Length: 243
Ligand SMILES: Nc1ncnc2c1ncn2[C@@H]1O[C@H](COP(=O)(O)OP(=O)(O)OP(=O)(O)O)[C@@H](O)[C@H]1O
View 1: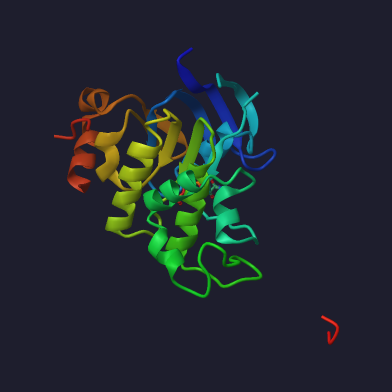
View 2: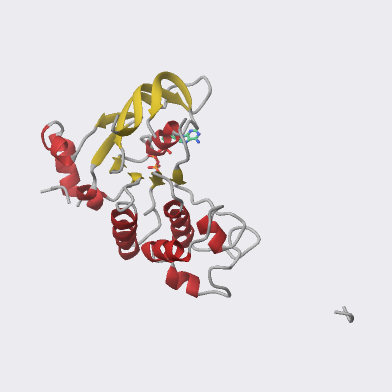
C-alpha cells in the first residue's frame, strides 16, 4: 500500500543448501521516509539489503515491491569504483547536470578533495589510475548513489571510514536535504546511533533475525533494554607530418 519493500517470513541463505543466515524476516519499509537498520557486527544488515535485491536465494516467504523491483540506488559496504573519471564515477551512465553534480558534491563534501591531485573531477581512479583514500572512495560511491534519479536509495554504512564532520555534513546535506525534498525512499544501515532521532523507521537485527520495527516511540515500551542501550551508546526523541 504505502510501503516500499515487504517481506513475510523470509528465509535466505548465502549457500545454496545451507543454514538460513536470515530467518523469520518481516520487513515493512515506508516509502519516501528514512529507514535505518541497526545491529551488531555480522547480524545480517548487508544480507538483508541484498536479500531485498534478490542477490540471496529465497528458501521460504515472499518479497513484495510496491514501487518488478525496479532500479535501486545502492552504495555497497565496500565502495565500488569504475575505471573511468570521477565525473563518470558519480554520474554512472546518467545525463550530466552541472547543478545536480555540484549539489551532490557539496552534499558529500567532495569539492576540496577533487581540488587536490593532478586533475579535477577528471582523474582516472580505481584501476588504471591513482588510488584514493578510503573516505574518498566511500564518498564517491555515496555521491553516485545520491546522484541518480531513483526513488529507492540503499546505503550500506556510508560512514565506515569517515570522521565526525564529513559524516555529519553528509547525513544532513545528503540524507535530510537532498533525499527529503524529492521524497526518495532511503534505507540506511549504520553503526552511528547519533542519527537515530532522524529515523522515521528503525529495523533492529540480532543474529540473522529481526528483533523490532517502528519508530523510537515503539522502542520506548516494547524493548526497554535496547532503547536504554541506544541511550548509553550516545531522551531519544525523534528529530602532424613530422609524426
Ligand atoms: N557474500 C557472502 N557470502 C557468504 N556469507 C556471507 C556473505 N555476506 C555475508 N555473509 C555472512 O552473513 C552473516 C552476516 O553478514 P553481513 O555482511 O550481512 O553482516 P553486517 O552486520 O551487515 O556486517 P558488518 O560486519 O559490516 O557489521 C555473517 O555470518 C557472514 O559470514
